[PDB]
Image 1 (cartoon, protein in one colour):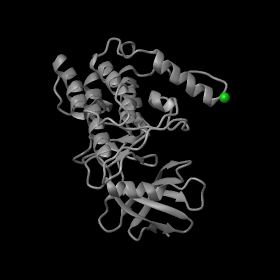
Image 2 (cartoon, rainbow, N blue to C red):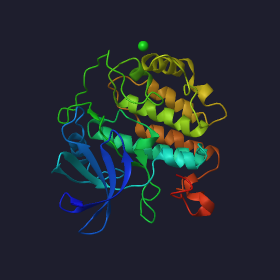
Image 3 (cartoon, protein in one colour):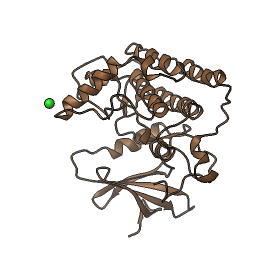
Image 4 (cartoon, rainbow, N blue to C red):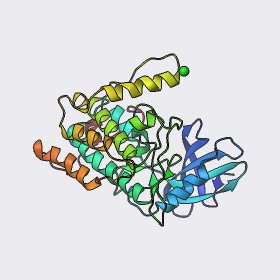
Length: 306
Ligand SMILES: [Cl-]
């Protein structure tokens, strides 16, 4: 039968692999587009139901999609959420694998705002990467605004009522993708708010430079490869990353790398820091992004770009 969750008809597939399947969908009551996340029921990595709960806790926060339904159907588990646009990694590719300073600053402060609100709801993200930051859809009011999806690695870092930080521990298994993960994550340390921020600084340099100096490294195994990547992150000073770039980005990475384990980061201080880049270069934070000039001004095309 075409319809799951009583009201959500399944359309084209937009992703397959370990995430069971992800589909396009439409609400059969109002026609609004949704994304249908299927997950095999009896599997060794059950994660969807908690991702639905996380969306419900973060419900209403701007930039976080709504969760409309979760339940059992067949031998699959379904999460229906707002369908959104391409990831920042997609637009990165289409923009020639480089964002200009204006776009990076504007995108950064929205990522700082999203992650902040996540922290306000007592959770750390722990999977920061450009592939999990999506823009809206054509014609929508939030078309070129940054969103945050995929919360399967979100963990509670403080008690919601007492606001008391989790204990510091070590010797944990390496969590996330090695290109953006913080240095503390490489060393197997318990993550916190600071690590979500340090991973953003890595993403910011990845947008500005088009690559990171610890990409394309070789090693016999993945354990040794993750260590070589972690090794160059500590060998490479923030100023060398920021070569020919506004030093506020090096200043940002250094300041969040120095944050104590339980310290609350000065989010607005970081946003003002990156905003002062635009004042230094005589630019305005008006919302104009690089991808809004693709294809002659049209935007991004489904079969040329992707
Ligand atoms: Cl090994």
